[PDB]
Length: 291
Ligand SMILES: CS(=O)(=O)Nc1ccc(C(N)=O)cc1
Image 1 (cartoon, rainbow, N blue to C red):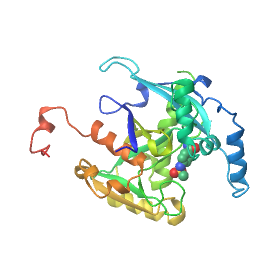
Image 2: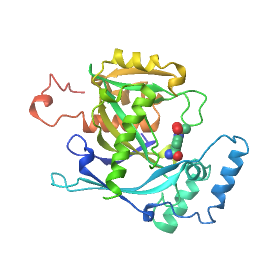
Image 3: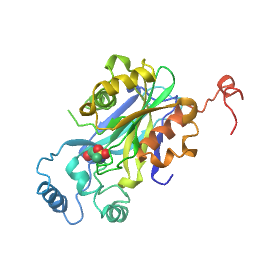
Image 4: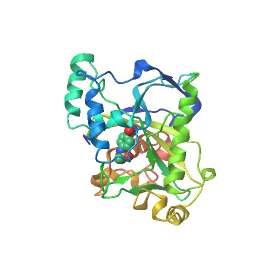
C-alpha cells in the first residue's frame, strides 16, 4: 500500500492521554520556502478571488514522535509539535509542486517535510457494542478523495506545561468529531486510546493520529442517531458497518480500493494494535483461524 506509511505503532494495545507528553515549540514549525513565503500568499489570494467565503484557521504541525523503551515506567510517547494553518497547507502539501518542495527539503535540511505545512489530522476506529467498526461515504463533489470511504475524524484547531493542554485538546477533538459527524451523545463514548501515527503519501506525507474509541450503542442505534440529524447534520452522504471479525482481511476485499489513505491507516493500526492476539487463549486456532 504505497499511499500510506506507518510513522508509529503504540505498545500495550494503545496509549491513554496520561502516558503522552507534547513539546509545542516554534523550532517544530515549517521552514520558510527557498524563494520566500510570497508563493503561499499568491496561491491564497488567487483562491479567495474565486471563493471569497473561504477562511484560514490555525492547525497543529507534527515534527516527530519518539517512543520510550517498551515496558518502561513514566511517559511512553513524546510528540514534537509546531503550528501551521489551512492557508500554508493549500500553498505546500496541496500544491502541484509539493514533490519539488520535498526534494529541496532533503537537499537543504536532510528532511523531506521541512518546507511542508504537514497539518496533524485525527481519525478513529469506532467500535459498536455489537462488535462492528463505523465507516462514512465521502461526497463525490468535494476536492480531496471524492466519493471514497472514510472513518470519523478531522484536523483540530489550537485553543509538558503548555504540552498537557495540547494532548488534552487532541483526545477531546477526536470525541468532538465523532459527536459532530455521527450525531452520537458524548456519554456513549469511551476515553480514546492512541493506536499510532500514519502518513498520507498522496498528500505529500501529512500525518494523522489514529485512535480506538468504543461506543455503548449497537450498530442499529448508531445508524438511527446518524440518520435522525438529516442531510444538514453531516458532511458524509452515508454510514455503514463491518464486523470486527471481517476487518482482519479488509485489505484483501474490493472495499480496500475505495478507502481514503487516512482510513487505511486507521484500519492497519486497529489490526496490528487492538487485533493480533499475543496470548495462548485468543491465539488458539478456533479463536484465531489460520489464513
Ligand atoms: C477537504 S478535507 O478532506 O477536509 N482535507 C483537509 C486537509 C488538510 C486540512 C488542514 N489540516 O489544514 C484540512 C482539510
